[PDB]
Amino acid sequence: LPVYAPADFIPVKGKGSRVWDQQGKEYIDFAGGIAVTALGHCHPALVEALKSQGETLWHTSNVFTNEPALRLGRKLIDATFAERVLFMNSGTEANETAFKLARHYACVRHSPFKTKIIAFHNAFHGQSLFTVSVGGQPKYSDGFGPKPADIIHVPFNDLHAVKAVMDDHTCAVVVEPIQGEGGVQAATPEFLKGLRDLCDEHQALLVFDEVQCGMGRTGDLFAYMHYGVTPDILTSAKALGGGFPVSAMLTTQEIASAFHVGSHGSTYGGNPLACAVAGATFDIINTPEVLQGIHTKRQQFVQHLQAIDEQFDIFSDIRGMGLLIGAELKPKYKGRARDFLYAGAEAGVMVLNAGADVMRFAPSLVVEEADIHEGMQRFAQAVGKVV
Amino acid sequence: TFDEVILPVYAPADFIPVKGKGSRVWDQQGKEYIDFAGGIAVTALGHCHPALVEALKSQGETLWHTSNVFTNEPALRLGRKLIDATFAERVLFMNSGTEANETAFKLARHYACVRHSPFKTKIIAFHNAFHGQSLFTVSVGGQPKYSDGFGPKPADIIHVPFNDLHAVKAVMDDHTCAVVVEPIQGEGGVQAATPEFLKGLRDLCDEHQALLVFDEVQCGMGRTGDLFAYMHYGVTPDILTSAKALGGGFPVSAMLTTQEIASAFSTYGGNPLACAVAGATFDIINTPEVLQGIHTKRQQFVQHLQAIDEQFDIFSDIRGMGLLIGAELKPKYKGRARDFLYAGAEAGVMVLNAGADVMRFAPSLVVEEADIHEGMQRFAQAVGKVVALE
């Protein structure tokens, strides 16, 4: 079921896209802690930001703002559709805030009865009771007592099904532009544009969960930029802090104004230390050169995956965007993704799954070409052991 | 700039802290403040404590992040420390108190579901409780103003008055999965559980096969002068949550329970960087000398508050435990806690409220005596300015 490391695989040190365990075994990291360490391990600029802000101020609570948070908010506002930002500590918290905001906006602007949230089968939005109920895997939301109601699930990429369930009582459509956990499935252009049009028609808010696909992962700062479809609310985490727990919810002034003092909050969220680190991360990722490199690097990975398939005949599809890569296993290898993952680890390469039938890769956005080649040769060796 | 950038959910002081050391903080104009607020009971060892900075830098050049597929040495070490020092046999690490409480409440629900019945779902919680602002945690929280207006709430949560054991007895039954309580309600006016109430919750949970869940996010990690408040009371919960002071300012949290309960789902999760910092924090707080000092320091604060009341006739009650201090305003000053908070800031001291009727103090557990005296002189001056007008 779940993927867990045995007692003899405990990471102790990381540098760039290499990780060492307690026994001193070296691994190439194509997993990034599940798409989190977007600039690799102990990146000098992030370490510098951590250490310098760490000497100055870590935390004051939202009885105050702080300079790192202000600077980061400004950067996100200048670079995106956002006019207002809220910082939290995790993707789950950012999504909680987004879903509460869409609900509350509908309640105060339209009607307390405008509560339906449309979400998608196989969606992943976090593991809080509300976010896991918006998530589209019933196995993970069962067994915790009464779920928050008025959430409807339809298939990802099925625009007709969305049209069928939406109405004037709908407050939000929540979608991952690419479903990372859900087999690395990208929205089609017509589907994503269709969501925008339906939200406009029903006065519902379009919420993009970009926790996994945002902050450079796709080769644009946010995936919405690739599609040219602007959401009402967007969430970001993971890559945002490069390994430091931080998240953000982005929206407009008109929507943000539905909140009042006390509508939401967080003790740690908006943290000067977190925001100093996320600022350094942002300054590196949001450059033409790094964003270009993500596309170059994607093709380096894809060519290796194609070569592996040519030799071993294991993949039916290679998909994703930028450095979120999915490789779907052929029917002959249905349900074997975990076995390829563990074989990878034996061979000294860390990879991911995206369901039992899909290999996933989410390396550092600055992973060195030499590391791509070495790690993919290790992965080819692992595939050879499995087949 | 705040109004131009952040969602309007906060009304931040009119100054911006840029630097902190110990219990002193400087704003952009170089104005120096004494910190009796601790970022709401978070910076339990003050700002930029050298041991915490050293842990941050050392782990920061080694390894920051692992996913929950893995453990890591800092998480293992912190888990061991918590297990050795408490009733816990298993520890799950998260980022925030809200997340720890989500985990605790989901675990109590799931344990009931799989060990008893899928119908065993009622959660008993208390008016004025604060457990976080996620949809589930705010619904377990006891302030309807904060849980209204987000659409359908997770159901099967019943609220009764804090400290009302009869009310708990009245609502509990075989369909009850949990009682959730803060041993001291920090946000809710700094109100401590009575001994009979807390022991009674334990007995009722035993009787009904429900789990007793202590939210020690605010009152834990040394705040009361014991490592956890449950230790003062001698009442052992089934599940306990911790955050705030745990990381001394770094975002980290923990859910503590037994092997029997955790099996329904010795450590799980934990950010290596967060856990390194929390390990250094734990090593300092969990010492006889620091814990003793929390009581000495409490009395230093309380004596000042008593002197302020003698001069100005403003407080009807001084309460709390250790370095969680509440001072309730007399009827003449009812609803005016915010006025004293702003006057405090103007006088160069950072304090808190706990509702509109109560002043709250949550300083560093190692706050220097000189800072206690200086900060309380500033607070006396602030009180003086307010009362001179009225």
Image (cartoon, coloured by chain):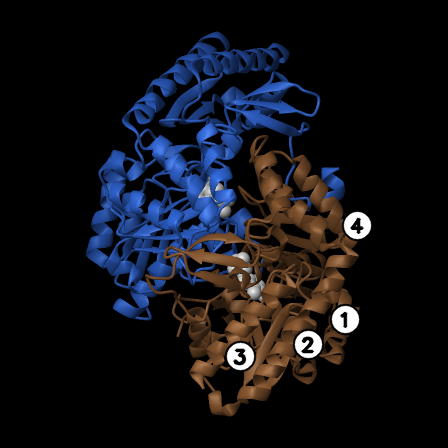
Chain colours: A brown, B blue
> In the depicted view, which residue is nearer to us: B201 or B113?
B113
Provide the residue designation for mark 1. Answer: A227
At horizontal 55% and vertical 47% (from top left) the residue drawn is B145
Q: Amino acid at mark 4?
A: Asp
Q: Rounded to the nearest whole Å, what is the CA distance between mark 2 and mark 1?
A: 9 Å
Q: How many C-alpha atoms fall within 10 Å of the one at disc 3: few (<14), some, or many (≥20)?
A: many
Q: In the rendered structure, which disc, 2 or 4, sits on the residue that comes first in sequence?
A: 4
Q: In the rendered structure, which disc, 2 or 1, sits on the residue that comes first in sequence?
A: 2
At horizontal 50% and vertical 66% (from top left) the residue drawn is A132
Provide the residue designation for mark 3. Answer: A358
Badge 3 vs badge 4, beta-carbon distance below 8 Å:
no
Q: Amino acid at mark 2?
A: Ala
For the residue labelled by badge 4, is the local secondary structure a helix, a strand or a loop? helix
Q: Amino acid at mark 1?
A: Tyr
Chain ID of residue with mark 2:
A
Q: In the rendered structure, which disc, 1 or 3, sits on the residue that comes first in sequence?
A: 1
Chain ID of residue with mark 4:
A
Q: Which mark is residue A78?
A: 4
Q: Nearer the viewer, mark 3 or mark 4?
A: 3
For the residue labelled by badge 2, is the local secondary structure a helix, a strand or a loop? loop
